């Protein structure tokens, strides 16, 4: 059912010659951008159509077109590691009141961690 | 006397006519230059 609504855009978001982009990283910036590919190949191009001159930064992954290389959209850096994506947890089951006792070792951790996050102006 | 001074004035006029042809050739060079240069390592001169 949800696939039928996305097939209408299939005449644009699919058959277009833009989307087949080659991802790479710009090694050198001259304000001419030296960009190194994943195949151990480099080239030099300029800005794109919607590309802003201040968006491209030194040492950032920048996707380019597959046929005629041109900067199209920037991408966040450090795309290689897949390991740290699973290190972030969500909603731990242990709550704040699960630690037994009134011991002051609890008060020391909340003031050095929870306090500056909740009340940074204190 | 007038012959020596006439050849020097017409010399700059002939260079100005050829100057427009060189400027047209420079535009052809700029047109022949495309953004990707790739990269090549020069191992010998």
Image: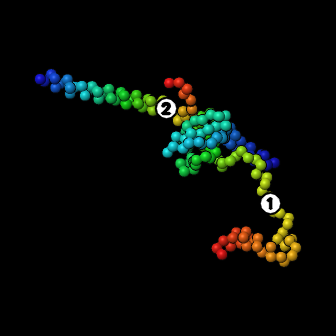
Q: Look at 66% across and 75% down and name the residue there.
A: A122
What distance separates the C-alpha of mark 1 from that of mark 2?
Answer: 53 Å
Element at badge 2?
A: loop
Q: Look at 81% across and 63% down and name the residue there.
A: A91
Residue A88 in the image, given as x and y percentages of width and height: 77, 56
Label disc, if present, on residue A90 of the rendered structure: 1
Residue A36 shows in this picture: yes
A90 above or below A59? below
Residue A8 shows in this picture: no
Element at badge 1?
A: loop
Q: Look at 64% across and 45% down and name the residue there.
A: A61
A19 above or below A95? above
Do badges 1 and 2 share one subunit?
Answer: no
Residue B19 in the image, given as x and y percentages of width and height: 33, 29
Residue A63 in the image, given as x and y percentages of width and height: 63, 42
Q: Chain of mark 1?
A: A
């Amino acid at each position: 059912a949800p696939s039928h609504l996305w097939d209408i855009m299939g005449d644009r978001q699919r058959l277009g010659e833009e989307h087949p982009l080659q991802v790479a990283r710009c090694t050198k910036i001259i304000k001419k951008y030296v960009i190194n590919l994943k195949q151990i190949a480099k080239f030099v191009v300029g800005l794109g159509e919607r590309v802003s001159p201040t968006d491209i930064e030194e040492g950032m992954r920048v996707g380019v077109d597959r046929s005629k290389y041109n900067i199209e959209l920037p991408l966040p850096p450090r795309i290689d590691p897949s390991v740290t994506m699973m290190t972030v947890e969500e909603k731990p089951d242990v709550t704040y009141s699960d630690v037994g006792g009134c011991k002051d070792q609890i008060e020391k951790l909340r003031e050095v961690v929870e306090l500056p996050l909740l009340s940074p102006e204190r | 006397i007038r012959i020596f001074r006439s050849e020097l004035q017409r010399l700059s006029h002939e260079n100005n006519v050829m100057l427009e042809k060189i400027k047209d050739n420079k535009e052809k060079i700029k047109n022949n230059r495309q953004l990707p240069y790739l990269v090549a390592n020069v191992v010998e001169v």
